[PDB]
Amino acid sequence: NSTQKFIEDNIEYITIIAFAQYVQEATFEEMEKLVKDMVEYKDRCMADKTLPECSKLPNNVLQEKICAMEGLPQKHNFSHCCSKVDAQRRLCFFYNKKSDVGFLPPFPTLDPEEKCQAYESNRESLLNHFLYEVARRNPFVFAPTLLTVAVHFEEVAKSCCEEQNKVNCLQTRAIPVTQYLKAFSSYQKHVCGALLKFGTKVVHFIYIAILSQKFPKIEFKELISLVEDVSSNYDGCCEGDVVQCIRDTSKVMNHICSKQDSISSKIKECCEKKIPERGQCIINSNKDDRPKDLSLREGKFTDSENVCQERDADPDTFFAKFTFEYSRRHPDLSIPELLRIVQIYKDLLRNCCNTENPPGCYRYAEDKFNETTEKSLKMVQQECKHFQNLGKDGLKYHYLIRLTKIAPQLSTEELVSLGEKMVTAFTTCCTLSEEFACVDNLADLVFGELCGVNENRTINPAVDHCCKTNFAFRRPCFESLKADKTYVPPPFSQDLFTFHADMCQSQNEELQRKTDRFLVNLVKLKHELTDEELQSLFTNFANVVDKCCKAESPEVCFNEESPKIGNKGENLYFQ
Ligand SMILES: *[C@@H]1O[C@H](CO)[C@@H](O[C@@H]2O[C@H](CO)[C@@H](O)[C@H](O)[C@H]2NC(C)=O)[C@H](O)[C@H]1NC(C)=O
Ligand SMILES: *[C@@H]1O[C@H](CO)[C@@H](O)[C@H](O)[C@H]1NC(C)=O
Ligand SMILES: *[C@@H]1O[C@H](CO)[C@@H](O)[C@H](O)[C@H]1NC(C)=O
Ligand SMILES: [Cl-]
Ligand code: NA
């Protein structure tokens, strides 16, 4: 079929993505040798379909070929994976991925003129190396996403190579491609992390909630059928099985498209498009309009006297149906808010169905939902007002202080990333009509990044408790945490807190990132201080920086005018 053709056609690209994600230390020369092995396997299976290995799991084939490369498992420290076979080997390979890609060099940027020359002379080589470099730095991003990203990156290179000011074009036009990649990455890590911590049974409520919001005219049975396809799709994609991921993604899009009528109205130009665009499209299409005849409630869950019986006959399906009906009627709610509501409903019924008069007790379920949602909504409203008052940077500094207090054991680079990701929820969403849904959806992804994808991280006991107990209530849990008062920092050199003359300028993100790192390191150093004292000290340093840039020889200015943060005898290090 078309999917098998797409895979056969793109086998070189597919192989690079898989190899680079699994073995992020592997060199580009090493990639080329695996490419030749998989092309050959592809040709062999075409010559002889009934041969044994031609019906094996795709990952089992790829991992066999990687493990067969002389000295490679030992060179990149994955010999322990190759000493296992089949499922145990697949699991080991999955555990081998590293979220922290700081062991890699800075992304190798080509000279714009040579990049353009390379694009015209050797296009396959350029895209091959791009895809290698992207995949090893984004080990959990799903293949259809990465291939779409490569396509868009190619359109950027093609268009910008025709312009006079090539550098400005490349830098500008790359921004939304990067944002796409980072948005999908965050979302995929969130779902995969949840799958590993809690299993498919808790997690497929996520897909019921999202699909029911997006396709509110769908029938329950068809939704459940689609949810089964989606859950399988996440199983393979979360594993890292690139071939199975592509196949299962194509199945989901075909399932959706082959019932366009009786699912959706707003996906026609998507059901035209190519693999894998037709599906990155469907994912980006907006929510279909609710059936005009859909009221705000379903009295079948609060007004019927059959609730406890329906629940008892099949609790999983009963709660799936609740999630379907409630989600499709509340397009304004976030996914985490819907899952909190499902849990509250489940807890409510545990109590009510064992009381003297259950119908009199569960009749008031919507009052419980109303209170919990009002609390969430008020919190978002407060955070959005704070954003309006302080701007992006000002709010970010408050988050950096709070996050560093609560999770000081994280690297500064990580804390800085988490702070930027947190503030982006507010810059993207505040003031929109679905502000609540947008903010809570995007904010929740931060704690998904924090809690880990293929590891149960051990940060500190309070953070670990929030990561591992209760997906839907994870953000509220994090909001309740106090500073970790057991923390004692390592020494920090005085140079971490020294402003250098080269930093005086107008810049986008590297100068932003330097300021952000300063604040985080300061908070680690002075963790004992109150948030207000830290904010005050930081604004002192900020004021001094601003003046000294407007001074000529800015660095002598900084050292005479900056506040001191050392204990009396400290010159080289601060403790
Ligand atoms: C991370 O934590 C999760 C949840 O505790 C672990 O997943 C469980 O692992 C046990 C034993 O391997 C299985 O019997 C359970 O079925 C798993 N539960 C779920 C919900 O998936 C996971 O193994 C941990 N990661 C490790 C130990 O590396
Ligand atoms: C990787 O394996 C080598 C060879 O046994 C070992 O010396 C080294 O310590 C290992 N490195 C890591 C990071 O595990
Ligand atoms: C809660 O109920 C009140 C009164 O009916 C209503 O005004 C409000 O919109 C509801 N809030 C939520 C979050 O549903
Ligand atoms: Cl990733
Ligand atoms: Na590095």
Image: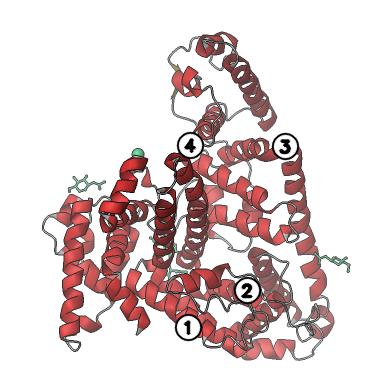
Q: Quadrant of ligand 3?
A: bottom right
At mark 1, the secondary structure is helix
Q: How is the image coloured?
A: secondary structure
**Mark identifier at residue 67:** none
Whole-percent x, y for residue 73 in the image: 18, 56
Query: Alpha-carbon distance for marks 3 and 1?
Result: 47 Å
135 shown above or below 399: below
Name the residue located 59 percent from the left edge and 90 percent from the top edge: 221
Which residue type carries mark 1? Asn
Closer mark to the observer between disc 3 and disc 1:
1
Which amino acid, by three-letter code, is at mark 2? Ala
> Label 2 near label 4: C-beta < 8 Å?
no
Task: Specify few, some or many for label 1: CA neighbours under 10 Å numbering under 14, 14-19, or 20 or more.
Answer: some
Q: Residue 554: x, y in percent?
A: 53, 13
Q: From the viewer's perspective, tell me whether residue 280 is left or right of residue 439.
A: left
Residue 75 in picture, x, y percent from top left: 17, 50
